[PDB]
Image: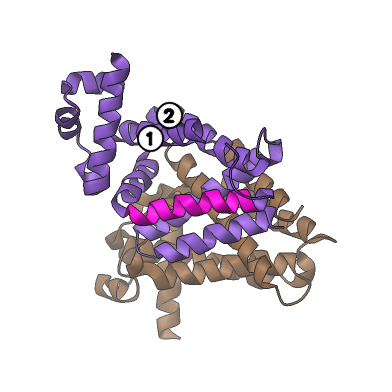
Chain colours: A brown, B purple
Amino acid sequence: EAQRERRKRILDATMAIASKGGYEAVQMRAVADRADVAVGTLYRYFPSKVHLLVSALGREFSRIDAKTDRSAVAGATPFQRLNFMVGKLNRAMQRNPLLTEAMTRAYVFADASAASEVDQVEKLIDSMFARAMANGEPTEDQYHIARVISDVWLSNLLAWLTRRASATDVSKRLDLAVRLLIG
Amino acid sequence: AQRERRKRILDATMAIASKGGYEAVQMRAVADRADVAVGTLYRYFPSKVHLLVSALGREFSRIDAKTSAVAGATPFQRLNFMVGKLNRAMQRNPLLTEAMTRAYVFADASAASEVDQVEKLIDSMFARAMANGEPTEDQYHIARVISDVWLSNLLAWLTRRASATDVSKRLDLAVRLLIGD
């Protein structure tokens, strides 16, 4: 529980710093200072700012997940239920632009050294989207569909990040993808 | 003869990228290889992103202009065939693929028009394969979904989070999910 509380402070600090200042603000020293941990302690659990940011996003997904029971996702059809989940996440993104910037940059820099962290996020977000579609245990294809929606999301955040697309554009792409996959 | 200078510039871009990746695509090197003055180069194509994006657009225009019906009896088969041929070409050209993936990652507002034109062209080619002809709105949209999956997966390959076989698999899954017979 001493490891767990230290991790909690570190990810809390990451989220606060990113939401306040974007990717450039998330410096390892700044995070360790805010979290009241020694820097080495920080590096041992999270060797770079990518690992911090992706781990923090994973934690947010699991908080979202845990409050999201089967009945909480509104909709009679898979289409309705997925659209509702996507819509909620889309609005959360639009409400938190600096955080979105920090996470998007973290993803562009994520490499093999962060594969475990990226994989846990991917597993989590795909499970959320797949369980939203499914009435019981999801099918292989519902997992695959989740992965497609997640790739459309990332590629369009790439365009947003470099100032070639707006929020109108990203939402538009997501809503098309969902409809084309399961409308 | 502007179109000759252009041809030589884009030829040099593709040759340099194919052999040496993104890092080899430098304005002086491309200028020298293309036998143009670097200033002439900087007038037509202000950065390496512009060079790489324009060179890609040219390849797809050539594929378009040299393409008859595309093999397959349904939209799925025709798109599966086309995606397959492009995958094989990616696999045989990893350095070129690296150059292009970096170009798109780094492309910003100053190359937005070039990027948009190339998108319209590549997606129309996907959609035309689906349609074996003039495509529906939906077919153009599907093409864009496939192009977004492709770029995301290329980011993962470039960063060693995915293999070339992974990218190929993900693209096949996307095709089947969107238009599968």
Q: Residue at image x 67%, y 32%?
A: B134
Main SS class of the magenta portion in the image? helix
Q: Nearer the viewer, residue B22 or A58?
A: B22
From the image, tell me which residue sits under label 2.
B114
Residue B83: image x %, image y %?
52, 51
Q: Residue at image x 40%, y 51%?
A: B89
Q: Secondary structure at mark 2?
A: helix
Residue B44: image x %, image y %?
30, 20
Mark identifier at residue A139: none
| Amino acid at pointer 2 | Glu
Q: Is residue B21 magenta?
A: no
First in sequence: mark 1 vs mark 2? 1
Where, by quadrant of the figure, is residue A109 drawn?
Answer: bottom left
Q: Which residues are magenta?
A: B77-93
Left or right of residue A136, residue A168 in this image: left
Quadrant of the rendering where the N terminus of chain A is positioned: bottom left
Q: Nearer the viewer, residue B168 or A8?
A: B168
